[PDB]
Amino acid sequence: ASPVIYQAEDAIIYNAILETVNAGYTGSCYVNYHNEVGGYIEWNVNAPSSGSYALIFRYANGTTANRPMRITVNGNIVKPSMDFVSTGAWTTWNEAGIVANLNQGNNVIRATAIASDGGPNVDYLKVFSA
Ligand SMILES: [Ca+2]
Image (cartoon, rainbow, N blue to C red; front, side, top):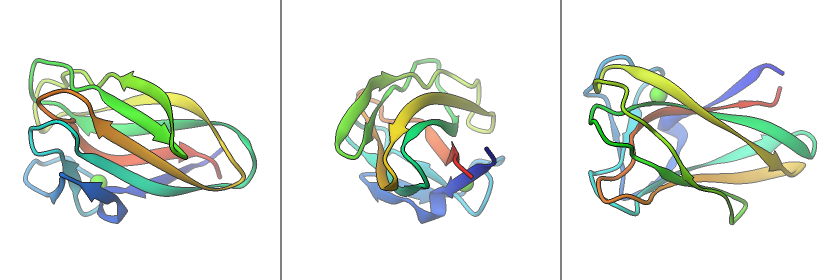
């Protein structure tokens, strides 16, 4: 499959902000989680058919500590604590990925900060669906 990129600029967010400070993001911005628990980002992701899809986040984590997130798909928690480990700098971007089942149609995919320092900075969500 070819990737479909769900850009930060198009995200639905909570206790998080669209930011452009740190170089190396793609599109027009990335999302920042406000250095606290509970914020999220979410997109409406089309699946042309039911099955397994790769969900890849491009992110930065300029701290030394893991910033894990809960991944929810259509209201069900598919990954209670997905790791987002240090990338070494706020300007160094890496990828983290999982596989999840999507339904034919729209899928609401959310990444929620579960740790006290919030989520990493997230560039986009890439889904191998096309
Ligand atoms: Ca971006």
